[PDB]
Every structure is written in structure tokens, then in C-alpha cells.
Amino acid sequence: AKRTKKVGITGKYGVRYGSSLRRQVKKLEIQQHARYDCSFCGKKTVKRGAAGIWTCSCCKKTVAGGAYTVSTAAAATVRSTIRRLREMVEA
Amino acid sequence: AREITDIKQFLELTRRADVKTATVKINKKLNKAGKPFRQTKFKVRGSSSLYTLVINDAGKAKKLIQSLPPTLKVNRL
Amino acid sequence: AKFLKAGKVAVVVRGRYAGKKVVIVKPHDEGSKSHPFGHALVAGIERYPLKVTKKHGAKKVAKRTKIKPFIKVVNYNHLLPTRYTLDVEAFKSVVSTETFEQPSQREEAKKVVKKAFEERHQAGKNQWFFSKLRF
Amino acid sequence: AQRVTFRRRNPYNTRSNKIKVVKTPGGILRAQHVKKLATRPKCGDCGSALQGISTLRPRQYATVSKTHKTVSRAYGGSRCANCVKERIIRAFLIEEQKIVKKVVKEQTEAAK
Amino acid sequence: GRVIRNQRKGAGSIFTSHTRLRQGAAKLRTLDYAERHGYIRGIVKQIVHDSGRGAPLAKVVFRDPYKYRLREEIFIANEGVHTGQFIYAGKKASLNVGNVLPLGSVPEGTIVSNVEEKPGDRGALARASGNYVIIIGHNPDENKTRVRLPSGAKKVISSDARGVIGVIAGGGRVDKPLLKAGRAFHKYRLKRNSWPKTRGVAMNPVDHPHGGGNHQHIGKASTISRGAVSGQKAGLIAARRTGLLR
RNA sequence: UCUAAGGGUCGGGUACGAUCAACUUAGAACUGGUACGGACAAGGGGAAUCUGACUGUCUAAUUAAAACAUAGCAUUGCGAUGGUCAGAAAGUGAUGUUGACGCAAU
RNA sequence: GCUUGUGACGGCCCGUGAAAAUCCACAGGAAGGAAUAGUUUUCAUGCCAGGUCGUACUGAUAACCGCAGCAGGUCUCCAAG
RNA sequence: GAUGGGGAAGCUCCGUUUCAAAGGCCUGAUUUUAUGCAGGCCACCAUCGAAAGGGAAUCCGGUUAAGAUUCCGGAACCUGGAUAUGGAUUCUUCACGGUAACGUAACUGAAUGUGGAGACGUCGGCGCGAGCCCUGGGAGGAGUUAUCUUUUCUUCUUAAC
């Protein structure tokens, strides 16, 4: 029973707001209410409490991150760029 | 507003020198299912509290009343 | 091989003694009528001697260095076994299951333990076992 | 079908002003003001309510014996006993490996 | 005439900031001996939500050097930090996300945030969520550093100015349509009284320079001189160009 | 006036019996001055046009609107020795417990 | 069943939803004290004091405000078949 | 909103810990006498601001022409202060038991530091309670009865601690 066809999670908004805006939110609100693997405890407990903060209910680690998702796009290439400049000086 | 269980401990407070007065209440109740009996309570008055002993077997309750100290001025019923 | 033995120092990680150091004296590896688990009789020190210094003379040194021991059955899971050791042959008779059961025999058996420990704290053998663990 | 009032001059339903409805010995329903409930004390580490402590309001602990306010482990009325189990593990094995580090700094002198 | 709405924010009565739920001023640590001659380690106690801001905060707890106690401070949390992380601070620290180093101590092409304009201001540049500056070059004599400000401007600062490694958490925030006037109401109740905005077009000749007329229209150019004077300035102020880009 | 369906507590050497207690639905005969949400309570509906997307707000005491607001769209100034504003002055102040994914002006 | 209290869960947010006095615990080990005898008022019991101003009644189709004994205005609790 | 400061011909304005020499504690040293001299400390450095927020502790019964969680009778509780008795502890000087969660009538603790409480949005159903509602057996009082009705109404209550 899939119920709705296109709108999915945004069915709560009804008919209002226009189709693009409702579809562009459906992009993010599937990210912020999604459940992610935990880089520490090895389970997927990770959920969002607020913009910026991502809380494991298993290992109780809190993890800072992106607003609507765990790891921002431009972040995962900072911790590689930072991983590379660190080895540059120590190698 | 307290209760005593052992008879002996009750005999102490009567001498505890804070106790000026006591009383004896008689209550007619029944036990188990069928048949009644005569229940008595002894209420000694402290400064900060009121202690009571409950005697459900009247074979004991009489030997106790005589045993009260003579200074203690008792109001029966 | 089996590193839980008669001399092996341990740390007590579970209950009222947690953080205090002991020595495994008579281990029962498997089985007993009560205690249906691997346990080890231990002896340890409940009070640690206070800092003694050059400046303390006269009677302070004897009253800083007072040790208060204990004897306890403990479960392995509640012990950290460590590489250190003690020479335990002094009280091997005085800390025993027979010592428990008749609790009078327990305060008779702290004396032979309390005496062996304040000896060693003179002649500084086992310097570490006498220093308060800190956490 | 009886109805009842506040016994105090606060007409309003605020957090302190709660009412419970009581049948007196004299046959009447009457309102009874109730004090705000007590919260259990928390582990300053893991946050889970640490058992063995009596749950009172803050100034009602001044009236209580010390066995209600404590347990007989080290860090008794403070940490949850699994937060004491760790910090013993962590105090022993950090200052264990920390001795092994200081011999290597004696070896790295003679090795070079 | 009347005093217009933007002239009315200066006296700051109902226009002040709504400060109640804010955890504090997020700053970096005072610059001291231990940090400029070496490093000092804290740990981040909890990374938490601050009201009115867009990015989370972290509370790292240092050990006071000269007195026995703990001291805990408020850092804008870089993305990737986690509670239980050691945060190293000082000249001799290492290059890892969250460690605050001087800028002279990091190679060019390094991504840092919450960088300082001058040493010891406890942070200025790139504090909003998702922002960072890149270090594009050094000037080892008459010490400076060449960094790229998040707008794209290129600024040159001191090389003793600290900054914390990584991107600020809370990236992606404005990707999500706000969708209704209510969600913009809950946004500015925690910030200040700016909202909603009446178009100066829709008001009277007293209320604004754009007001009046039997149609709604500005009537004169909407670009105003930088050398304008108090209350004349409404509209696009001292613009070099205007109109949609191509 | 009946029929049916839906629950519980209970003893079984290592299939059945009993009792207690509910407002729910569906079905069938009969019935009457065809009456039965019997009073009360309780949407009129449809084919189009102009116009503002919507919720919301405003001339208290002649105007509730197609007007203001809004999300969305775009432009503009500003990297703090600063942008926008205040003060008679100031060892003065609001944005700012701020830092371009920000503040200010449209 | 209705009213209110509470507990464990769940949803929502570019919104994550007061401060302080006050009280307690823990870490530490300053010191102070057993043997002819020395403590402890966080165990029990016992003893003394607990001041100042408010307290009546309406709270409204006549006790408040609207020139008034005005069909207006005015925050709140309880709630039977 | 004072103070210190800073403007202002001035009425007064700024600001609220600010460009400040901003203060009184814990007991050791005294057994000429009480507190000199002593080490150490702690730097938060006015005050005002809520009868709905935070908060030490009280309940039932009776009483007046008019007052009561205040008066009466009884049953509690908190706080500040003084010391006395019993128990407990002490020769292993500052308690024991349980593997552990932890237990208990008690069961030393200064400067200092840290942790909890105070201390918190909203909605949704679910659980458990309290008062109310309904209701059967029994013990009483009242209303109806021309006929029917093991009948209709009412009292069987239990506070803080």
C-alpha cells in the first residue's frame, strides 16, 4: 500500500504552496528524517535533533554535521584536503 | 501518631519522664469471620508524639493495666 | 597460561572498594557450592597511608602510615588482573574460606594481614601496591 | 455533584497551585493543595537517574539521614557505578601505557 | 515629514536582539602563554543548539593553567566534531578538524573557519554555517597571510591570528524552501524585530521616500548616492550596476 | 419480538466444562391513518467570467476589499580602521551574546 | 465513561522551548582525637523561641469602569442525571 | 538604577563592572588578655525589579449576629538555637554486610574543586491512579398505593502526618 504517488512526505502540505516548492522540500525532508549509520557504535541510530546536531541514541555520541544531512558535500572534501595537507608536512 | 508492637517497649515510654498522661480505649470488634472480642488500646502521650499499643487478646490486657506506673495519670475510655 | 594466581595483584572495579588494589590469595577457578562462578579470595588495603615527608618526625609518621586492610570473596569479572605481584606466603593460611563463616575469624585475620602490609611499607618493596589509585 | 474551591488566594491554575480532591472525615469533598513532584538525582556523567538515592525536593535533603543520599561505593551519590567502572579502567590503563611511553623516551636517547 | 522605518532602528527600542535562549557569546580562547608557546588540550563536553544562530555550538572544557579548576568555553562547532573529542589549541598543535592553530602554522590550501582578524579578538571571519576561508599563501617576512574570505574577497591578515580547522556545521541550511509565513515568523522571533517588511511603495509620502501617488511606483531613481544623508537613503544604495545578471 | 457475531476469569497425569461482565455491528418476522434525524439540532446545489495563489492582517465608532502581509524571485551596500542608524555632548549607543548560508536597504 | 494528576513512548521545528537564590552529594585530605579510657547533635529521645503588615464583603442584569441602581466592558478554578 | 569615572552654561545625560588602591573571611599563633601578629585564602565587587514564575514547614472536627487552613479541641511538621540521656564507634583509632546492582538506626572531614536539584515547548494516542458517575446484597429514615411496583428518593463517611 503505497498510498500517494508523487508527493510522499509532503502530502502533509496538501494542495498549497506550488508543486516545485513542495517537491524541492521533499528532497530535503527525506534527508533530515532519515536514519543513518553511526560511525562509532556500528549501528544506525543517528537522527537529527536540530539544525547542525546529529545524535546517536546508541553510543550517545553527538556529532556535528550538515543542516539537513549528516555529512555536507563540501565537508567531506575538507577532511580529505585536511588529511592530505597533514601528510604533506609529516611525509 | 506512632505505634508500638512489643509489650516491653511500651513499658519503657511510660517511665520515659516526658510522659505525663496516658489513656485506655476499649473497642468492641470481631475477628476472622464469625465471632467478636474486646480490643483495647493504650495511648501514651509524649512531647512530640503519641504512641499506642493494641492488645487483641484480653488475657494480656489486664496484666498490663495494673503494671502501669503510679505517677502516670491515666484517663480510661 | 593462567595469570590469575596466588601473588597476582588486581584492582577492584566493583563495589564499595572500587578503585582499591588487592592480591589474589586463594583462587577457586571453577566451582563451589555457593558462588557458582569463578571467584578469587583476595586481600587488599582499604585505607592508604598518607603522604609521609622529611618534615614529619616523631609520632606523625606512625599515624600517617596506618593501613586498614580487608579480605573479600570477589568475582573475576570485578577484578582487573595486572602484571604486578606480591610475595603472599605470609598470610596464605590466614586468608581462607574457613576464615569467612565465623565473622569473628575475619577480624582475627585482618591482624595477620594488617601486620604483613605495614611491614612491607617499610623496606619499600611493592612501592606501587601502597599508593592510592586515582580516578 | 459536589464542587470545591481553592483554599488559597491564588485563583489561577499555575504550576505551584495544583489541587487534589479529598473526602474528609466530615463527609465533604474538599480540595487539597499538592506540592510539585520530586525529580530523581542524575549521574553527572551518563545522565541516567542514579539509583539508591531518595527522590525529594532540594531542601528536603537537609532533613534526611546520609544513607538515603549516598551509596557506599567511591563516588557514591554522584556517578552511576558504570561511570565509575570506566574511570577506574581508564585511570589504570592510561597510566599503564603512560609508563611504557617513558621507557621509550629513555631508549630513544640511547638508540639514536 | 515623518521619521522613516530604517531611521527608527537606531534608537534600538523594540529592535534590539532577542537574547534569552542564547548559550553565550561564541568565542575562541584568550591568547596566553600555553597556547602561543605550545598547545593545551580540552575535550568537547556536548555539542548543542544555540538560539538565533544557524550553526551549533560546542562546549570544550580546558584546564586553567595558573589555578586549580576547569574552564569551559563556547566554540562554534566545526563539522565533524563529536562529544568525547580532544580539541588541541596552540602554536604546536596538529592539523586536524577542530584544532585551533595560528594561520602561519598551516600550509596553503588549508580550510579553516572562525578565523581572527587580528590576533586575540577571539574570532571574526567565517562564523556562519557552512562557511570557510582557504589559506592561499604566506608572507613569512613582515609576517602576513593571504586568505580568501567566504564572499570571495581576498584579505591579508597577521600570521599570529588563530583559526580553527574545517567547515562550520549547519551546511545546507538555506536549501530548503521556507514555504509559509509562519516558519519565517518563528525565525525572526529569536533574532530581532525586522519582520514582516512593508514595501515603502505602499505607504504615504510621510512614511517613506517611495510613498504617495495615484499609482504605486517610485518616481525617481532607486539607486541612492553613498554621499546621501540620514533618511534619504532607501533603495539600492550606491550601486555600481543593477539589474539581473547575465 | 427474536437470531448472529464479537471478551474474561478458571482446574487438566510428565480435546471440552463453568461462571462473570460489557455497548457494538449486521440480519429477519411482525406492526401502524406511509409515520419514524417525528420536538430540538441541522450544507441548497450546478455551468462559467473578472480578480487576489493560499492561512493571516487593517481604517476601534460609515469602507474587510481586488488594498497591506506572505512564501518564492531578484537586485543592492558591507570583511569591522566596516555597512545601515542614533546622540546636544561623551572615556556614547542599537544591529551585535553579530561575521557573508550574516546584517542592513529596496 | 467524565474531570484532573502522573509515567513511559511518539510527532513537530532554518522554532529545540528562562534565570537566580537555596539545598545536597561527591573528589580531596587540612587537621583533630582510642587503652583505665576519647568522640559523635546528618541515629533516637528530650529542652527553648518562632517577630512585622495583609486577612471582613461584592467580584457584578444595583458594591469595579462607563456622569447612574447603564442590556456595555472585565482574568480565573470546581462542574450532577 | 546609584558608585568610580566621562559629558553638559545647567536642569541632568551616558553607563552597570565599567580604564578603580572598590573587601571580610577562615582559623593557627595567646593561655600576661584577649585577639596581636600569623600562612593561606575567595575576586562573584550596590541596589531595585513577580501577592500568576522559584520557594522551609498544617491537617481534621467544632465554633460566630458578622472572623477562621488564624479561634477551640485534638493530631502533626519546619526552622534557628542550646545543651543532656540511651544506642552506636574506638585497642585493626575514624562501622560492617552482599560476587555485584547495593544494603543499614548511627558509622570523623577544613581550604578547594566538580556533579545533581531548583530547571522548564507542544501535540498525539497508550498505561496507571484519585474524586465524580453508574450500580448489586444488607442495615435504617421519608414519599406513593383506586390497582400494579422484593418499589422510588436519602444516610452508611475517613484529613495532614
Image: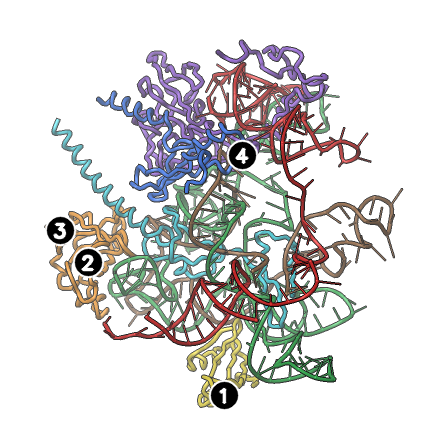
Chain colours: A blue, B yellow, C orange, D cyan, E purple, F red, G brown, H green
Instruction: Look at mark 3 in the image and give the residue it sits on.
Output: C3
User: Disc 2 residue type?
Assistant: Val
User: Between D31 and A26, which is closer to the camera in this rendering?
Assistant: A26
Q: Which residue is mark 1?
A: B36
**Point 44% across, 31% down: residue:** E55
Do we see residue E68 in this rendering?
no
- Who's the residue at 23% across and 23% down the image? A90
Q: CA distance from mark 4 to mark 1?
A: 79 Å
Q: Quadrant of residue B11?
A: bottom left
- The chain letter for the residue carrying disc 2 is C
| Residue at mark 1 shares a chain with residue at mark 2 | no
On the question of residue A18 being in view, the answer is yes
Residue carrying label 4: A15
Label 1, label 2: how far apart the Cα atoms are = 62 Å
Q: Label 1 sits on what residue type?
A: Pro
Q: Position of residue D6 (x, y in %)?
A: 64, 59
Can you tell which of label 3 and label 1 is closer to the viewer?
A: 1
Instruction: Evaluate if marks 2 and 4 touch, with contact meaning CB atoms under 8 Å apart.
Output: no
Label 3 to label 1: alpha-carbon separation = 72 Å
Above or below — where is A3 with respect to E29?
below
Depth check: give the residue in front, G66 or F22: F22
Give the farthest residue toward the left: C1
> In the rendered structure, the residue with mark 1 lies on which chain?
B
Secondary structure of residue under mark 3: loop
- Whether labels 4 and 3 belong to a single chain: the reply is no
Q: Which mark is residue C42?
A: 2
Report the mark closest to the observer, 4 or 3: 4
Q: Which mark is residue A46?
A: none
